[PDB]
Amino acid sequence: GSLTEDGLSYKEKFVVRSYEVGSNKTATVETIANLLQEVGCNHAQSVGFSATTTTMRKLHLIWVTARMHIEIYKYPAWGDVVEIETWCQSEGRIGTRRDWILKDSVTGEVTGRATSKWVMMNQDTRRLQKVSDDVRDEYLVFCPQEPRLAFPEENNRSLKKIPKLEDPAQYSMIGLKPRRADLDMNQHVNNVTYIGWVLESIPQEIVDTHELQVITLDYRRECQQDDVVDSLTTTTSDSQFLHLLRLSGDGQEINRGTTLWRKK
Amino acid sequence: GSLTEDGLSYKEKFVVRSYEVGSNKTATVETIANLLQEVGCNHAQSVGFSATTTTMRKLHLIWVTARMHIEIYKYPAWGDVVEIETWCQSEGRIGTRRDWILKDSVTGEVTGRATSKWVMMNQDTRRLQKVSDDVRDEYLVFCPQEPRLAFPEENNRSLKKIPKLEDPAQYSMIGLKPRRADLDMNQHVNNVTYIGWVLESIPQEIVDTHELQVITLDYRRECQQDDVVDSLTTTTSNDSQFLHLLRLSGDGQEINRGTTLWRKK
Ligand SMILES: O=C(O)c1ccc(O)c(Cl)c1
Ligand SMILES: O=C(O)c1ccc(O)c(Cl)c1
Image (cartoon, rainbow over all chains, first blue to last red):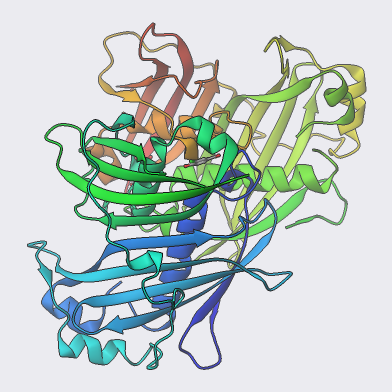
């Protein structure tokens, strides 16, 4: 991987692995989400991050994911090479955004795109915050100053508000628990694990006859290492679904989302 | 990755990823096990498999894992490059073996080694069998003819018989279930998922003060997609050793047994 000529975006190529593909012999959406996080981390390292800036370390602040939105046109097959370009942009004091574009390395065609929203949090208290001028100033040195959007269109799916699923859910997968492989180096549940848990309650017949085209996921609260989660899904329709992840006991919401599937 | 000059082994380099490392900022043993399977798959593809041979496809036969044995001296850090060399060898009619050697790409030092035993099974009936002469002759053209062992030693750990853990277990993790990401392209539970499940019942205090040096795992029966597993561990021992058992949550049918050896950090 390398920063591009202008130093305002980063590109990396990945060869799809045998264990990264599903029943269709193409990369799963969880594999795609892991590659997005990997190229994001390599970009952060290339421009001087630990991921935190110097002012953030002084104030004990961290970036936390608020939303992930991914649209896939074609999933790469086992052995194929996918090139992913990523960049960040400040969104004033709301937070920051990281966008991605995925391409078939051979044809150069766009095979997918993604966008994510990040908010500032005090690492100790876990209290959300607005971004200060100091953090925005140092962030502006590695971001394009004119807007660059993976999802440019006004009123596009990536910004749509997601409603809360009402009981009874049409489908459910209960008692989901993270294992040590689901945790990151800081013992926090990996963001991709929540995508896997959401998809667990999609019925097998849909997975057998459709391919996932779009997923939008809000992250409200973290699942701790000793927590247990229930995954709930209801058909809202192409097939569309509404999703809810909540703690198995008291029902505290941890994520809500929507998926759109197209028939094979 | 590429076959070596003589065409009897395969090498591949991997850059360790951010999500592949654990609390020590080095690759987990599950990451190592996934890289071993990946270089094994790339080797099989480079020598014509599709991982069945022509005679196996005609007779509806497949290779299934019987045992995995891994020893790690040093785990690669995030961003490091690890080079893995792999090769296969026939073991007469018993089955086949795949061995691996892991090296630090910069120093060229050996940082780990692994060996696995595979047995032939009919894909439909699931009945184990001996290797036929046609299959033995077919894969002999891609294997070294003089023995090449990752674990050459006289009475080495890789071949040690593993006993069955007796109840009550000292530690347990109950109700483990595979999710869709734990399945391979044929909807079978990935071999690395069982390693993760074994390790789940090791207490956190051991994980915080020790590093895993050796794991030996026998595979007896598969966990199906709708099965639920219980992971059981008992301390058998500056080094800590454990005995492991994975069994179905309901009737207690054994699916795996193993041992781990941990050295203090
Ligand atoms: O292999 C598959 O089809 C597969 C894998 C993961 C996942 O979450 C889904 Cl919905 C399907
Ligand atoms: O992050 C770790 O320390 C880690 C990860 C996986 C695993 O199985 C164990 Cl025992 C530890």
